[PDB]
Image (tube, rainbow, N blue to C red; front, side):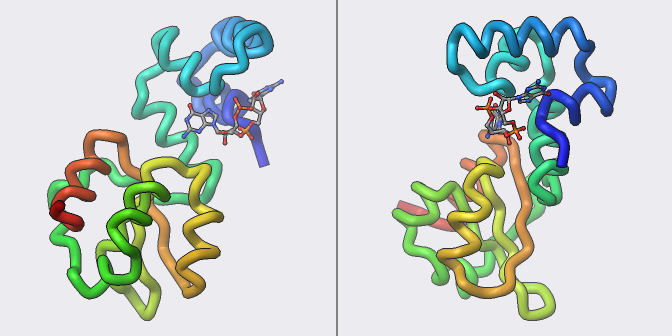
Length: 137
Ligand SMILES: Nc1nc2c(ncn2[C@@H]2O[C@@H]3COP(=O)(O)O[C@H]4[C@@H](O)[C@H](n5cnc6c(=O)[nH]c(N)nc65)O[C@@H]4COP(=O)(O)O[C@H]3[C@H]2O)c(=O)[nH]1
């Protein structure tokens, strides 16, 4: 398994000098690497695509075509969907389909769901739009 920086290098979306500059700053700041890379010019979608591939998630280019299944939304309390950044949207072959806001949460969510699941990753704005449609307040 590759680290995020190596992944982006392999995909040609950052240079080695950009990575080394980010990693030297990270050693001096503690900030998340992806956050530093984006601040320095990496497209945020480049970040999420690499983060998706790293955690074995399907990157969702859009959430606009998704009609959330109310049955699937019941599998998580709204407050949990929010804090875990997970939207269950439907079912496929006996697995629940779940759209995450942060790939670092995949394991915490998968353990909670305790059932076969298919995980997707969406950009922040797209995720929030999907969450509000799935969990009206
Ligand atoms: N939602 C979100 N998740 C993010 C972001 N940036 C990184 N991550 C994810 O969070 C984990 C922790 O990243 P880190 O704190 O910067 O800690 C990283 C970083 O300090 C460092 N390092 C990361 N990439 C490289 C690299 O390419 N070369 C070298 N020498 N060190 C690296 O290794 C540690 C673990 O790397 P990873 O396996 O890739 O594990 C990463 C990665 O899966 C972000 O901006 N948003």
